[PDB]
Every structure is written in C-alpha cells, then in structure tokens.
Image (tube, rainbow, N blue to C red; front, side, top):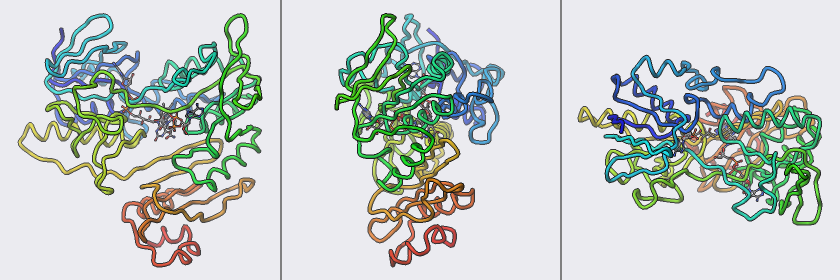
Length: 432
Ligand SMILES: Cc1cc2c(cc1C)N(C[C@H](O)[C@H](O)[C@H](O)COP(=O)(O)OP(=O)(O)OC[C@H]1O[C@@H](n3cnc4c(N)ncnc43)[C@H](O)[C@@H]1O)c1[nH]c(=O)[nH]c(=O)c1N2
Ligand SMILES: NC(=O)c1ccc[n+]([C@@H]2O[C@H](COP(=O)([O-])OP(=O)(O)OC[C@H]3O[C@@H](n4cnc5c(N)ncnc54)[C@H](O)[C@@H]3O)[C@@H](O)[C@H]2O)c1
C-alpha cells in the first residue's frame, strides 16, 4: 500500500497537464502520484495518428511528451522525479473503491489517496461489439496509445506497397486513410453513413474531402458496412466482406469506430450523465475529493447552459488546469471561476487542415473556395440558430482567420441577413 495526498489515475494528456499545474501550485515531494498503464510518461496523443506515422521524419518520443503540443515545456520522466512526483507506469488499476479511497492494480498492489483525479480517457470501441466475424485476425489494428502506434508502424513496414482497408469515417478514418496513403498503400475507406464525419461535417464539407481523397487515390465507400473478414492459415486478415457482398482485398485493416469514456471502475460510485462522469464547473464528481477530467467528464458547458462531454485534446488540457486550480483553491479557502469552455476541434490530413469552434447547431452556410483541385483551397461554414452564429468551420485558414472564426463562435454575433452573411463569407468573421 502506497499513500499519496493526490493521485491522478491515468497517464495521458489531462494527467500530464494536471501535473504541470500541480508543480506551478507548489506541490511537494511525496504528495502527488500518477498511475498509468502506459510504459511512458504523458505525451501529446494527437501525434500518434499524424507525425508518428510518417514514412520519413516521423515523430518519436521523447519529442512529443506534454506540454510541447501547446507551446509549453517538455516533461520527460525526470521532470516528475526531480519534483518528487511519482510516475507509476505500466500499472493498470483493475478495482477502485471510492468509499475507502483505495485503488487496486492487476498484480494486487494497492494505492490510497486523499484527492483522486480520474483521467482515464476513452476506450477503443472494437468490431467485436457488433459481432463481426474474423475481427480477431492479425493486422486488424486500432489506434489509441503509443503501443498501438508502434504495432501500426511495424504492420505498415511489413505490408508496405499493399492494400489497406479503413473501417470508420470519423477522425481516425480520415487521418488514418491519409497516413496509409502517404505510406504507399492502396486505401479503401469504408463507413455506413452517407458522408464522412457525420457528427460534424455537412454533406457539402464532406464532399470536398471525398473528392480530395479520391484524387489522392483513396477509394471512399459511403453507405458501406464491414460484416466480416477473411483470414489465411497464419490468421492474418486477407479480405473485408461488405454488407452488399463486395469483398475488398486487405493486407492491413485499420478501424476507427468510436470511443467511450473509460468509467468502468466507478459504475455505481459516481453520478453519470450521457456515458460520462458528471462533474460541476470545477470538475468535481458527486464524491467529494474525486475529480474527473478530459474525455471522461460530463461538465457544464457554460456558454450553452448544458452538460457536455468533449473527447478532444484542447479540452483535456484546459480541464486539467481547472481541476488542479479548484483543488488548490479550496486548500486556501479560495474559489476559482467556473470553467468557461469554447469547444475547439481540428484535423489534419495530406496538405489540408481545418478548425471548428463552438456548436454545430442550426442551419449551415458554406463560404469561400471549396474546389478540391485548387492548389490552395480555403472555405468555411457558419452554423446559425435563433438569428445568431453558433458554430464556425474553416479549411485552409491563416492563424488570424482561425482566430476570427473562433471570435465569432465565442461572441455569437447576430445575423440580421443571411444574404449579407453569404456575400461577406470569411470577411464577416475578420471584420467583427
Ligand atoms: C490516435 C489519436 C489521435 C488524436 C486523438 C486521440 C487519438 C486516440 N485526439 C483526442 C485527444 O488526444 C484526447 O481528447 C485526449 O487524449 C484526452 O486526454 P485524457 O487525459 O482525458 O485521455 P488519454 O487517453 O490521453 O489518457 C488516459 C490515460 O489513462 C490511462 N488509463 C486508463 N485506464 C487506466 C487504468 N485502469 N489504470 C491506469 N491507467 C489507465 C490510459 O492508459 C492513458 O494513459 C485528438 N484530439 C484533437 O482535438 N486533435 C487531434 O489531432 C487528436 N488526435
Ligand atoms: N483530430 C481529432 O480530433 C482526432 C483524431 C483522431 C482521433 N480522435 C479522437 O479519438 C477517438 C476515436 O476516434 P474515432 O474516429 O474512432 O471516433 P469518431 O466518433 O470520431 O468516429 C467513429 C465513426 O465511425 C462510425 N462507425 C460506428 N460504427 C461503425 C461501423 N461498424 N463501421 C464503420 N463506421 C462505424 C461512427 O458512427 C463515427 O462516425 C475519439 O474520441 C476522437 O475524438 C480525434
């Protein structure tokens, strides 16, 4: 049994950014521990679907350890031990008892805390959840952690020059199809929805990327579903069978069909809301001294007066700082302001790069140049509900053009005329 005043459960992005805030708040040696099932100190997870997979000049640890992804300093394992912050790596907690403040690992080790910070992130939904035949064949890969990224880098070198199938049309589907393409793979994207990124992209935004990906040689099969996989004698995947009977040849298969908050250790012990652990504006759960941050928390999104859950890296960084300030603030009888978050999402693929700020509610208006064969495409979209701008998307924008649409999403300016908004386009944001 090891006791610590503060225990961060998980060693991902929120854990690393909470550790940075703890050091900034004068944490003392022996006070804080980070328990992680990963063998490495916290890192900027977004690099795993991008830089990590490049055929040349690839991103490797320790380069992308936190907090460099936000322009902060690198926190190598020594950053922690110099401060008396115990990193407990390769340790998976299989039981958590909030009533006795005890965490129990797979090997039966126990750890106690005074303050717990749940930062377990998201699970990887696997094709077994839909009873897909052959989903256990070798080379049917998923991407969540650095070990998955290493197994993917190796399968890429092994099957290079061959055929890849990507099941999923979300973030992983779009980013991984691009990764396999640049790695000399013949890629097919498969997903059941009528267009890519259905939870964010309109049919018009999606159509730009479908045409773009097609010209790069990526076959995008909309309205398609994988129902099985063929495998050879060694058990390696050889093909992907679709609901319509079409069979695609596959040397490697990559799947991105969503993630769920990794809350399994606390079911029945914390209040929940839409899959996540329900928190207040300071990330404290229904149990005093227990906080939940990043991907697992369903917190009040102040701007929209609703409880929301965000499974993106910007929120994992901002929520971590909020919970640590809330814990340290209470120790001095002080209160900190409520979390005031502006949902910020982004994706990168090929020579493209988009940003989204706010909420994708109401009706949309496409602006700019959305031609996929243009050398420098720049186009965006606005989301309008109740006469005001709620959301703003922009592909190919400059730093100041991205901050202009972010300003629009924060301030929710009124739209007296949609005809004028369509006519101004990106200038509506740049002016305001
Ligand atoms: C490959 C890939 C690529 C991207 C992204 C995700 C993925 C999977 N994201 C999403 C973003 O990385 C994500 O929102 C943050 O990692 C969330 O930070 P957390 O700390 O909440 O979870 P995160 O998953 O980072 O950390 C959870 C940690 O808890 C550990 N853990 C869980 N259960 C445990 C247990 N029982 N015992 C011990 N340890 C345990 C995990 O092993 C991990 O170390 C993204 N977002 C974005 O906006 N832009 C981007 O470009 C990307 N790119
Ligand atoms: N740039 C980024 O923001 C980025 C990049 C990579 C990963 N991520 C994060 O990592 C996590 C995993 O991403 P993801 O792409 O797996 O999730 P996702 O939620 O973005 O997309 C999964 C998509 O696959 C669809 N799908 C579900 N079942 C399917 C099936 N049987 N066949 C095909 N498609 C199916 C879903 O409806 C959804 O559209 C998420 O939390 C995501 O936000 C984010």
